[PDB]
Image 1 (tube, protein in one colour):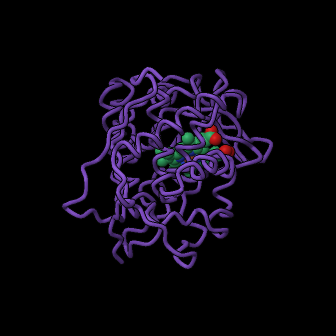
Image 2: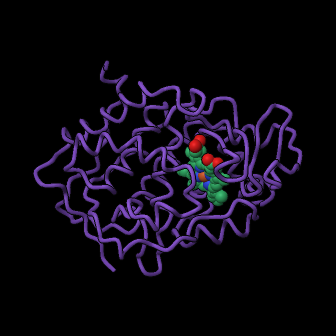
Length: 291
Ligand code: HEM
């Protein structure tokens, strides 16, 4: 199953930087969403969920085709809550109708991280919309009530190794869980809309208590008011994961670098890039632009 990247006709860096800016500006202006957390976290969750359907065995799913736009995928119960990120982007697609769904959903994720003071994520254009019949079935995203073995095994299908898995979960400790959404409730840390390595720190230095939530699900709770999913907590149970958790807790920059590489790989899985394709773009932030 081959998916070759095709640059949107005649567009270049400037075109996409325009699209970046538009997303970044609305991020700035629609600041009260989710109790003034903003749309950042939901955008990077959306970029991960549309990429997380990929299966390295037959090259199905993945971000290439933008199939989250079809009812089947849009209505995946594991995607509950993502409708708000979709609706956020909708005005922008209208403003820039030449960009493909897949490029817009993945650039939304890159924009959020950079605007929330995360690392730069190089990004490549060229995803191409594919028909509804290419939509992956529900069920390829991970469960939260499982263990390390589960986590390790799951991510193998996305060709992610241990270091890559731990960098990706870390995920700047952004946003929170919502009971109505996932049957989980609460944030991973104090800065839910600044990209940091706080998750690693919190994991290792909080006092966690295994409790049941109002959705009758167990989660780990801290006196500080933070929470961890069973799959999150499993990272300190596994001896291989734990060592990496400790490395990222002790080195902000290493973590920043590692995440950038894994997130780009995640966004690019399944896509074939012609040698003649353009190099990846590195977008400047609003701040770097003085906007
Ligand atoms: C074993 C893997 C993972 C599991 C089981 C999982 C599960 C969860 C669940 C239960 C939520 C709550 C959704 C809601 O209630 O609104 C969620 C939120 C989110 N996750 Fe994941 N996830 C994992 C991996 C990832 C990774 C790899 C990233 C992205 C790089 C990611 C980014 C997010 C973010 C940003 C949120 C917060 C969204 C917002 O605040 O609305 N997750 N995750």
